[PDB]
Length: 240
Length: 234
Length: 10
Length: 9
Image 1 (tube, rainbow over the protein chains, first blue to last red):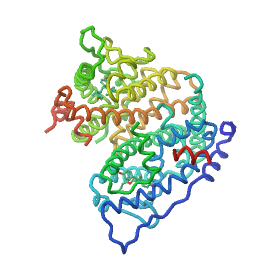
Image 2: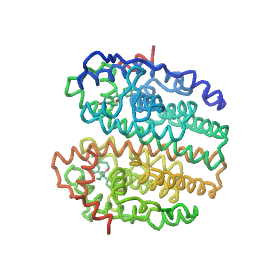
Image 3: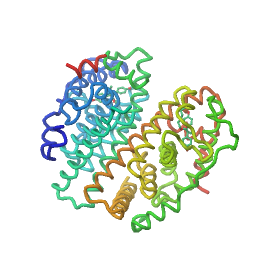
Image 4: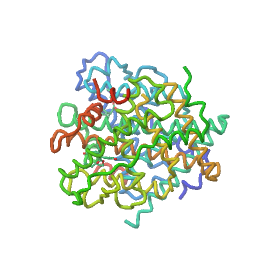
């Protein structure tokens, strides 16, 4: 495996180089939007982001070492966590707002336009606020995103010591986080505290993803918000 | 007002947490292995209802928790209660691979789970978590630290909680250094344990969905306490 | 009024 | 299966 041979700096460089781009929405201020069509902007955006995420995942060290079945499973488990942590990252500098796209910046007032989204909105805002107070670094963010990809579906016969390989890569990403923090001049106590602070965020990201998946399944059944074939297949994986 | 939790030493934090532990409760002494969703879900919600009373009094004894307002205590417990039951379940299931020890007289295996719609999937997730804890040789002192982290973290969306959370991190590291681990093994193990908390969150959210579906099916009456704790998740 | 409110006061 | 095909391409 190439993943296990990388140094911490080579790991960060690889992850930084694999970053997907920030996409634009189809939002138009002159166009009236309904709750349905505003949510349409977000599901259309997420669909386009998913294509980039799939090709990003191939560049996460260790991910292509896995079978195709396992790669499918990890992305089916983690895709909304990964979209959401990216959303939170790019919203850091916009307190009280979510930057879905450079042309789509929404506050809580617009989050209440669609019913049932206010809570998820507020949770995303709280997570971004937490990143801002921690002064989360881009190098730490790309580490957290790869951990989500590898970790979120690892616990969902003989052959599969694939789980062992995933665990050794995750250990390497932990080493990489600690190296970043040591270079930031943190004391060892501060390094362990910050590492814990970052990993506990992942629990909240998991929570928000689960709640988002529930509302997404609801939006499908209402059959008013367009959902792409890929989104429907991703959503279907979380139901069976 | 300053909190006593921050002045505790690591060994005092560990002792406080061990002494706060609730007991391991029993199910009914009926010797019939349950298979129907009726008897199974009756036994499990009855057990959870009794465990919740002990959990609330355990939470009051977690350092820093009583420094919070009543409203914040309510919120954290409403957010975290099923995660806390589930991590307790997987802890006491460690020494029984392939089975879940809901109580010393209620050990269930995968075959009973597949007689209840939707149970097998959460069953297998719980078993995998138990197995992972077993293979990491998770210690009781580490377990009570993680359970307190869940209580304080899961609904934390506060400066006081974050300082208490940091103190618990200090305490986990202290235990691992006391157990002889190298510096690298310490942060690697700390990461491994905290990443399992993401899976415990996932199992709680899946279980909460199933408990609500069981509520609407009205298959067995639920306690008012269990219903309000469930209701808080909507 | 929640039961949890009462039990946390005991 | 779309995700399967995109991972294979």
